[PDB]
Image (spheres, each protein chain N blue to C red):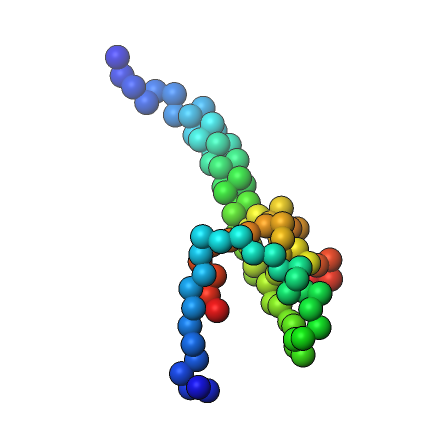
Length: 49
Length: 49
């Protein structure tokens, strides 16, 4: 729901963001602190969705 | 026997060492940026920002 946004923790995985990048199914695809095409080079832990 | 007889020389050495130490420590300030390390911000964003 709008005021009860679902929260998910993602960790201990390998995921390709290029399949997310090239996909046109997303009307808005906008990042803030990371370049979308650099997401497969450096990496982090404890992803929140 | 008596120590602290050579004051001025020690003061000179301490002043120089302190200047170098604060100069080195200044390398760890964001100065208003997003990070204090340069390789990361190279490998985290696009040229425009």
